[PDB]
Image (cartoon, rainbow, N blue to C red):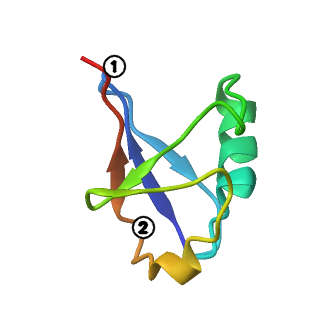
Amino acid sequence: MQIFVKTLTGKTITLEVEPSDTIENVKAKIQDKEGIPPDQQRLIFAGKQLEDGRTLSDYNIQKESTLHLVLR
């Protein structure tokens, strides 16, 4: 049910979610941690690109795998 996210800051952040983890759902959860618009933010899972708020359970998300985002 948990989900792991890695930041270039090395700060470990944990979200309370279900495996459906819908990005509109996860993003909004992240909006609270830090301001990030879902319609503007996209994530990646095991090389797979997560969408605008598609469901993660459908993505067969695991025990809270770590998703990492990079732009450099």
Q: Can you identify the residue that label 2 sits on?
A: 64
| Left or right of 59, for residue 24 | right
| Left or right of 19, for residue 34 | right
4 lies above or below 55: above
The foreground one among 28 and 9 is 28
Q: Amino acid at mark 2?
A: Glu
Secondary structure found at label 2: loop
Residue at left offset 65%, top offset 65%: 54
31 lies above or below 46: above
Within 10 Å of disc 1 (Cα), the crowding (few <14, some 14-19, many 20+) is: few
Label disc, if present, on residue 9 of the rendered structure = 1
Q: Quadrant of the C terminus?
A: top left
The foreground one among 44 and 32 is 44
Q: Find residue 41 and report its horizontal and vertical position in percent.
A: 59, 34
Secondary structure found at label 1: loop
19 lies above or below 30: below
Q: Quadrant of the N terminus?
A: bottom right
Number of marks: 2
Residue at left offset 57%, top offset 54%: 51
Give the spatial CA distance, label 1 vs label 2.
20 Å
Residue at left offset 65%, top offset 54%: 23
Quarter-wise, where is residue 40 in the image? top right
Residue at left offset 70%, top offset 22%: 35
| Left or right of 36, for residue 69 | left
| Left or right of 17, for residue 50 | left
First-in-chain label (1 vs 2):
1
Within 10 Å of disc 2 (Cα), the crowding (few <14, some 14-19, many 20+) is: some
Q: Find residue 53 and report its horizontal and vertical position in percent.
A: 68, 57
Q: Amino acid at mark 1?
A: Thr
